[PDB]
Amino acid sequence: MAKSPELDRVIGMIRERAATPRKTTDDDRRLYETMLGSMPLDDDIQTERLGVNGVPAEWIYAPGARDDQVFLYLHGGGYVIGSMRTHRVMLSHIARAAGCRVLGLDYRLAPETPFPAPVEDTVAAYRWLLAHGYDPSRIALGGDSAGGGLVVAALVALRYIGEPLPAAGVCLSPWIDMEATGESFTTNATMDPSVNKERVMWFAALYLGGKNPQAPLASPLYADLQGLPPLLVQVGGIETLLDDARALTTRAKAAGVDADLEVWDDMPHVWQHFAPILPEGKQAIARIGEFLRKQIG
Image 1 (spheres, rainbow, N blue to C red):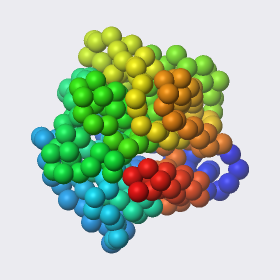
Image 2 (cartoon, rainbow, N blue to C red):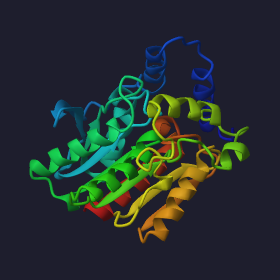
Image 3 (cartoon, one colour):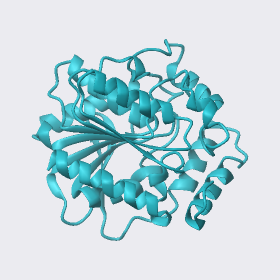
Image 4 (spheres, rainbow, N blue to C red):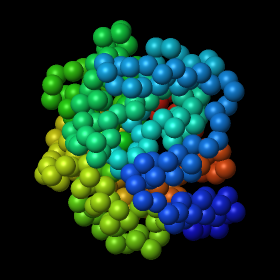
């Protein structure tokens, strides 16, 4: 899209997957895994599969990690695809940069289960952390795309049910509006190689299972954001989801939340996945690390 061989290669990988033939839900899941999950973890990364209050999950951490600091992470994929298979490498880089443990959730996906299952799962995982003696002031929630919206919905839900809120939230290209009403869905239509309004609406239909698309916990564009901890919002300048990120930040600030928006010029959706081969990916991951160190450290 822009002029650096690194970015060209990435935009290329993206435009390729987008044009690979697929027939089924699991084809789409597998293709994502092929695109984003084909590189190994560094040899020094430790992982463990476990259940947290019934939710399948994975500890991910690098040497030197503070075992009392937890980044509870909610992967993207439109609430339909994605998993630790697509995300664990990116998460291992964030873990190292922040010097903390990541707890990655393989939360329930649509169409098998609809909204609000992922909110339920995030609440369950958080309650598990608390029950096991982790301190809210040392926990942050993070996520990308659907998972970025889920961070906000889960924080609101936690407040609504009286759980002690964590120290921070990190939202990477967050999806906060099921109806894709953002003007960037038009403005960046020709610029965004991976996300467009039609696809967003399709995934929304699958996730919602017939429920109201403006439901605050599906579309936190409509949620009460008061009381939330500081948020870091990153998004790419060519994204159709750009206005989702802008709206989240604006609405959060209006509700008295310490929210900060970073728009990274020329970057595609969740460009951080491509940190191994993209400078801006590593730079954004370092920034997340600094934010986490300032909030849960």
